[PDB]
Amino acid sequence: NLQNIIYNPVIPFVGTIPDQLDPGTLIVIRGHVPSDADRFQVDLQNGSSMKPRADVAFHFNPRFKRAGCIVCNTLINEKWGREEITYDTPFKREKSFEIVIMVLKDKFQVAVNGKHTLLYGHRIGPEKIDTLGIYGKVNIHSIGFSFSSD
Ligand SMILES: CO[C@@H]1O[C@H](CO)[C@H](O)[C@H](OCc2ccc3ccc(C(=O)O)cc3n2)[C@H]1O
Ligand SMILES: [Cl-]
Image (cartoon, rainbow, N blue to C red; front, side, top):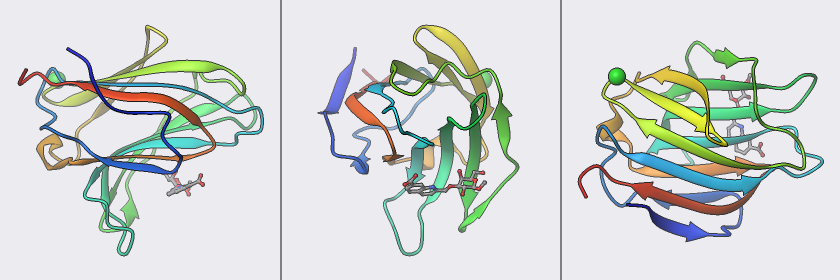
């Protein structure tokens, strides 16, 4: 069911998601963390506005300092909510990954390299998400979608 919208995108990458993130939709991101990365993020956005900054329904932000972590949050009207921090991170500098974001009715469920990583409850209805941004120090081989409407 997987339709990649792009291979080997230049980062930063911002792309329109070509259908609605209905429950059962998968977002699949394959890539590699450079040796010098401090952080990168996958943002599921309401639009692509830079000024002012588009709302981010789902900010998925691996951080590499110390023992590393993943920060998840929501940006509404240019303000970050309560940080959801996962200390058990599968990401490492100079290692490849596959991220699978599963869009469920009430939350995202994220697996990396085929291992469950975290949950994140919807704070913005996922129907308002139309854009995917990838920012920071990360190399991306592919971004695709398996839409539950197909
Ligand atoms: C703790 O401080 C804030 O925490 C936010 C999540 O709670 C976010 O992770 C904030 O980062 C927002 C942000 C937003 C847009 C970005 C675009 C590019 C880059 C970059 O890493 O070069 C980084 C960018 N970082 C971070 O500054
Ligand atoms: Cl759910």
